[PDB]
Amino acid sequence: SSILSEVSTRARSKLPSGKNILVFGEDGSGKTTLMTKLQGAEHGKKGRGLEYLYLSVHDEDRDDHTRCNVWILDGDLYHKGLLKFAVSAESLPETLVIFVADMSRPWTVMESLQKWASVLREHIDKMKIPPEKMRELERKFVKDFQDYMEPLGDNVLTHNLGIPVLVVCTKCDAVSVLEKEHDYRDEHLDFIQSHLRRFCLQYGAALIYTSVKEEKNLDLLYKYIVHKTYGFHFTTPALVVEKDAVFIPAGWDNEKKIAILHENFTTVKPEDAYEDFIVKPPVRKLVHDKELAAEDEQVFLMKQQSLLAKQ
Amino acid sequence: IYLNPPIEECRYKLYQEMFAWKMVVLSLPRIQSQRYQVGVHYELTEEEKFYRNALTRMPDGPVALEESYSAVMGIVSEVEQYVKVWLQYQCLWDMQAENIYNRLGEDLNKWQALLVQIRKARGTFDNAETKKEFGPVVIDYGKVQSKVNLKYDSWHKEVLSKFGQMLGSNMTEFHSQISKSRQELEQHSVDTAS
């Protein structure tokens, strides 16, 4: 009625809230470990299906407190419908989504990402967003990408959902172990890095390496998350100098900035299928010993009937 | 107006409770022949040693999860709505009555409308109830029950005073002009040549 006008008009200074950061990833990737550790608690409890984390972001510059909603999603496809509980129309425009590719198993990176490339995409249209709002947010995100200062092209954002997106590859410490235990070549690191950069480019995604065991760039990841979901001041440069852990700001990417990384490796020119140049991790567990079935009385007895007939 | 646990707690704790009611039946160890079948010389994987597939063995499909979370998206959503209502009383501390007076200058008489819905806005408030329950979530308005009470009481008092003040002014208009017109009628010159 009349009150709902008058009292609402008396508004004071606040900070935007209700933001909804979403994490889909392949199961067994330590997604929960990363999100919990960044939250501050070393690790909550895991489980099945959708999980909730209220990420408390405090701004000392304004001295305020806010909570974003980490809706971390289970990896199994049979738990894909419950994603309707994660993203809806009133929540969609202010959602940021990060996929997690556990580098402990590089052989399962791209398709897992590409699984996301289906799932969220499907979920973004099953909800039937009206075309005008999807279009306006898409062009808004395109502009927000283009104005990076520390672009346009055929594949840049060539298919995207118009909300900010990251590809946070966890467990980067493991790259050392799988380097020596597998003789996994450094040029292969360059190849996965370039392919991930092409993936993030066609989604305009900012890519970040991070290692929980090394507590590496966790502060940087927090900074970037707060910068994107809120719009906080950002000062970190494009940390791409060392290959152990890299931070690719959304917009720093260019086709030539991937060409330079293409140049240094000369093993197999990168158009090749990701999976081919990486080596499959062979399955360890042996197949169960075959059934020692007993021949039934009937065909057995018929066989002895035949034997006695031979007599 | 604060939430001592933020509204996200109302959802996180319920999710933990649901997780407990799932683990009570899910984390059961799996019957396995490896007790003597040592031929699989490998540390039993968590997703088989602990029998973590029951969610996919739904007789009714995943609808169960769909309903469960839905209940939560019921329970939390509307209760946040209730929380929202309480936050609306924030205005009792940061508002200018001059703005209201200017906005509703010369209403039905002066306001006569919001002074009616304010009495209804005494709802969610000024009742023997001290804590609103809903399911397993109880939101207790104990610290504010008297504070917002005193503020809203005084504010309603002042609005009533201003309203009734100009109402009395208009009734002075009422009686004065009625009496003067009555005297004019009481001149009673019914027959006159002019």
Image (cartoon, coloured by chain):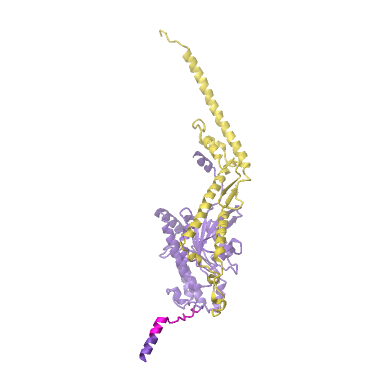
Chain colours: A purple, B yellow
Horizontal and vertical percent position of residue B86: 56, 45
The residue at 39%/82% (across/down) is A299
Horizontal and vertical percent position of residue A96: 50, 59
- Res A256 visible: no
- Res B149 visible: yes
Magenta-drawn stretch contains A292: yes
Locate residue B89: give its quadrant: top right
Q: Is residue B139 above or below residue A309?
A: above
Magenta-drawn stretch contains A69: no
Majority secondary structure in the magenta region: loop
Horizontal and vertical percent position of residue B94: 58, 42
Which quarter of the rendered picture does the C terminus of chain A lie within?
Answer: bottom left
The residue at 59%/34% (across/down) is B157
Residue closest to the far top: B193
Residue closest to the far left: A309
- Front-most of A184 and A56? A56
